[PDB]
Image (cartoon, rainbow, N blue to C red):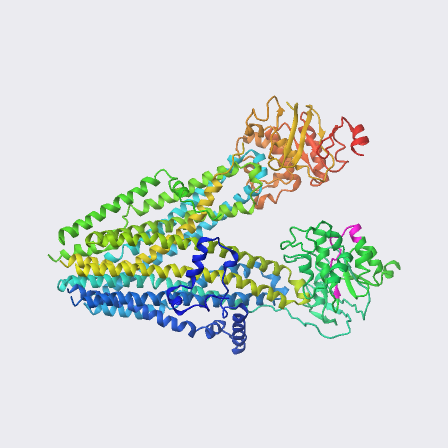
Amino acid sequence: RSPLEKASVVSKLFFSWTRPILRKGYRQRLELSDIYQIPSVDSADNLSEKLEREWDRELASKKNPKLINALRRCFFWRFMFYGIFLYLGEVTKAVQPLLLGRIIASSIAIYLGIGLCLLFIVRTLLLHPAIFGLHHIGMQMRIAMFSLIYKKTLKLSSRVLDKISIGQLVSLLSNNLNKFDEGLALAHFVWIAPLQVALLMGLIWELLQASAFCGLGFLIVLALFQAGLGRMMMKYRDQRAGKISERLVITSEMIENIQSVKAYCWEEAMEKMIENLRQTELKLTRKAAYVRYFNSSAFFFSGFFVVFLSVLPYALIKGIILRKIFTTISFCIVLRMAVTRQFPWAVQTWYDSLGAINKIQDFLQKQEYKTLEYNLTTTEVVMENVTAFWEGTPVLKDINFKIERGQLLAVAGSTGAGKTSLLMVIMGELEPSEGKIKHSGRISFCSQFSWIMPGTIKENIIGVSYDEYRYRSVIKACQLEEDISKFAEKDNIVLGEGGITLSGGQRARISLARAVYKDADLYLLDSPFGYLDVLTEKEIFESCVCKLMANKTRILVTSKMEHLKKADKILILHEGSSYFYGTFSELQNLPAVTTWNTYLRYITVHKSLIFVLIWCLVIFLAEVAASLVVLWLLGNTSSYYVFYIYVGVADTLLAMGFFRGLPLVHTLITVSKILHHKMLHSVLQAPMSTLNTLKAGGILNRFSKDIAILDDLLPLTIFDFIQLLLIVIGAIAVVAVLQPYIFVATVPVIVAFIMLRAYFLQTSQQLKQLESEGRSPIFTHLVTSLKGLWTLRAFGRQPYFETLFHKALNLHTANWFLYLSTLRWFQMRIEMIFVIFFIAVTFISILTGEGRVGIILTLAMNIMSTLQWAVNSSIDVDSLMRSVSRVFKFIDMPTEGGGQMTVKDLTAKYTEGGNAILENISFSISPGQRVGLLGRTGSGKSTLLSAFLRLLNTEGEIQIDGVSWDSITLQQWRKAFGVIPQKVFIFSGTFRKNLDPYEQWSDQEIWKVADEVGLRSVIEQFPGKLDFVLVDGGCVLSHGHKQLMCLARSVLSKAKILLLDQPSAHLDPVTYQIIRRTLKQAFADCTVILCEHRIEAMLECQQFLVIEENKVRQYDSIQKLLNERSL
């Protein structure tokens, strides 16, 4: 099924293998089934077997067991030929300048023109094919390492897994998701660098043999300077981490508590708080990027200075002909790339791969979980002299209990008894320091929480065997069929992992049903009735817990007395000591939208953005005229060649000035700051209609990561694209005018540039989006499988678990290779366009003074590498700009817009015109009274409180305080009503700052109110006087203190209403008595509405406003409510 095998050799050289697949994808949409079959050798199981033998052999080789050698052992000569072949191609590109110098001496030279074109043709085929081949091994190496991690995680013991955090390996696993795969192409760079450096210097020495050391010294000095900036840059970025973490916590608090923030009527205060932290953080980023910007300019402004310095030492003895000058300049650019781009990057990248393998080898040693599979036995249980620790003394001592067959075993204990560890020790999942135990081969387990993977009931039931009769008989016996009464697809009801979209009680019953319906050599139930309550527990006890499991010899743990009554024995532990162990009678004995139009608006979002950008364009044509005029003057004593070298320096001719690149960096930095101010203000203005629509995780993730990318990563490469494009486009123009018809050739050549990029981007954008989309399933299965280790290890279904993961990695690999193969296909065809232009340039120039011909000839070889880097940068531009467009979409957020009061015809709905939560509600609010708004609680009364707050997708006519719901400002109306929060979100800061961020309260008004509110005595022990910073979201203050803080804030706000709800469910008796002394005086002249579910909690209300479904009733007193509203 793989088109690669059914392909011709020419398709491998011409990249025609992906030509048809990409062509078909250009018309139709990116179908998920369009992914071609993976290579037969690329099979996950086949690759895993080869690495498994080496890994076992590596450990068996010696005590040291260098796993890195084993990985190289099976994959060394596979790429060793590629490294040698690549080095031959790299040397060929260097030899080209020597041949180009022969033409400078001049007919017969036409023979050299074919060779110049031939050298590029041979190099083009070798380089592209080598790149595709080399990258393939990187995926193969990464696939085996990624798969091997799953095997290691499947054998670790609880003693090591619990001690080590999840981020030790799970986070490290995602670190190398694309590092080693993409970077595998730099393995042979170091080896090629030594030979190339000597060869390039040898050809340079063949010309003068005197100033050879001058060129190497300049490169070494620049390399040290370039490296030194990175050390400061990395440290500066590391220093910026502290400010980023502080801002992120505040942003999360605002995002999570958006509902409270809107009620707090202090959104502008929260906006100002984030502003102060962001300004200091932006100062570090602007300075750090400036250091990188100055360092990045080194390469673009190095060739002219280095070449001129080396040339002068040789020119001192005698001024050589221009042929030697051109040869050195061409070699210098190659030498500059070799000394800066083809060596400095390799050293850093090469050690990165070694470090990952060291970490992989580090995790190879860990506490392994021993297993005995299934040993034949008489199904007898035994336990005596058991001793172990929770990891300081033994949490158990002399646990003597043995059962021959069929004995009813039961478990019991206090809170935190730790019997699960003893049960794990009984099953072998916990290490016993002493004692012995005889148990049957297999055993059935039951966990407290079911970490069932995504799938239907039938999918979970069919784990080792599927039975039609059991699917009906067990479902009725386990009440699963009864729970299926709401299923439309019957047994085909599949949900996600974690049981998010399933009944909580039935999920545990259904999960235990698969183990209960399946036979086993032993049974070990733990918290089987964890969710069953009253009727469910009684039904299970009388029909499933004791009737269904009657025949099988089982040991269970439960708190039901009826279940214990059926048990023949019971063991009770009391703080590490078994208080009772025996019969029961013993105790009773005593998204991918590419809008080019929207790009201009984002680009033109700064005051000086237009002016700064236009400045470089104005200077762009300015330098071109001088270079053309200098050539038109000189070309149309000893220092004459200096002007030609300076003019011939393409990098220097288009080099950005000292006051050119820096201004763009400063201008680009302010763009993110302006966007952040607009985004923060707009986000707080989102109405509940749209605020509740967006997921909580989709806001911070689209704000924390997006803001950093647009600031740090974006401007660093954005300026490079403009800098590279200016030189590349400008250089061709000078040659175009010089040749008689190069403009005609460029006219047809420049048109082909759009066709290649646009067609490739059509599939590349979809492939990149599909590649990231499929990565989620790998992470989703990894976490889900890790949590359910104990349940899976009980049955030991490793082969089923291993098979469940081997196929998953293949799906990501198939999309990865297709996206990687297509990426090279566009790049491979790109070199063909340049070769044709280069051939046309040579032909016209040859048929055409030697300075003009020589300058044009030099620029021909000096545009190859620049064009390649230019095309690659333009592709990634859309990838980074994609996040900015999404932020702009978020920027278009929808706009949000005397106790006597009354309203009528108030109908409210949570959604826009959805089900009417309120149905023409009308009520009378007499001042100076307490009206309990209770009723049929338990169906959700938050909407009714929100209805009085007008925070729903509806509207009304609230004739409160002499004003209408629309006449007065919403912000002004927001200060009228006050509510008691259910879970207050106090700002992380000092008590004075957190409680009154607006700072409108005076110190006298603060100190006196604190004593008056009664919180001063409780908060007297705060650091200093009251400046104790409430770290970790106010964890220091209690729930009553938060209510007291809520009372303190409300008292200062002088709110006319006090919407209290769920008081008894959150307040302590001491706080309630304390509140009764204060709230009575605080609301003595206010109209509050105290709602609650408990009838006793509503007995304190003067009136009895009993809420009802879709029609809130009323009662003037308890007489009518207790007679009609209650029943």
Bounds of the magenta segment: 523-537
Q: Position of residue 623 (x, y in %)?
A: 22, 48
Q: Is residue 447 magenta?
A: no
Q: Tell me if residue 979 can be seen.
A: no
> Is 914 located above or below residue 541 in the figure?
above
> Which of 479/114 is in front?
114
Q: Is residue 529 magenta?
A: yes
Q: Is residue 353 left or right of residue 470?
A: left
Q: Please say whether residue 975 is visible from this viewpoint.
A: yes
Say which of 631 and 583 sits in front: 631
Name the quadrant of the C terminus.
Answer: top right
Name the quadrant containing residue 902.
top right
In-image side of 173 versus 851 (left or right)? right
The kind of secondary structure the magenta stretch mainly shows is loop
In the image, 703 versus 366, the foreground residue is: 703
Q: Quadrant of residue 425?
A: bottom right
Write the residue at 66% across / 39% down: 1040
Name the spot of residue 1120 as percent of width and height, x first: 79, 28
683 left or right of 491?
Answer: left
Answer above or below: position of 233 versus 603: below
Q: Going 47% across and 74% down the picture, which residue do you hit? A: 74
